[PDB]
Image (cartoon, rainbow, N blue to C red; front, side, top):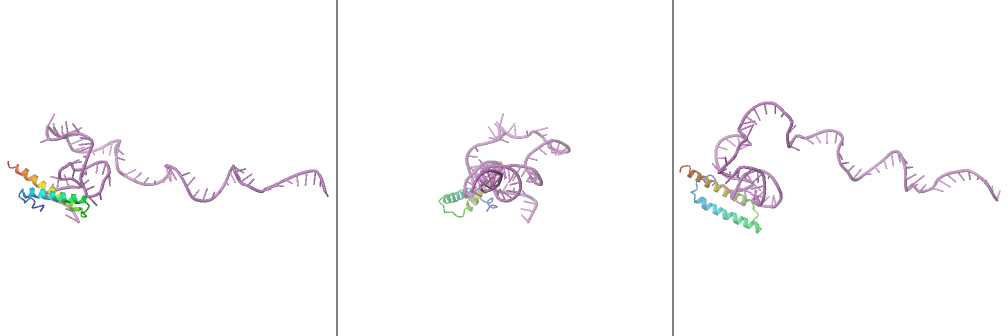
Length: 67
RNA sequence: UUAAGUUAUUAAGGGCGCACGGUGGAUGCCUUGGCACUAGAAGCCGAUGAAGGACGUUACUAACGACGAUAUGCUUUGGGG
């Protein structure tokens, strides 16, 4: 993905962001209710969201390099 | 059967020697933090938030980094294995 995340159509990114945020919410919710036992997913979901915002920022800058 | 002389026999204490304590840094070490030389800057920012912080962020959490809700980091170019 993280290459062709840049190939996504700027609404797949938007829906992808909120799907990933619901996934992170469920993970944090079941870490507390103590049944997770694979705690490394939390970190990588965070970084995915980071990935997804970064490219969605830079489209914006290139969207105003022309205008 | 008398006059006389004398010593230990506790070492409570004293000096010597012995042997384990407490103590803390004499020896060696350190070189993590500066005296000074050379060179480079440029003294150094921002009304694009400038100037030190406060709260936070790790799967687990107690001070500095990141700076930061994209948070114990994100993308990209080049090194590197």
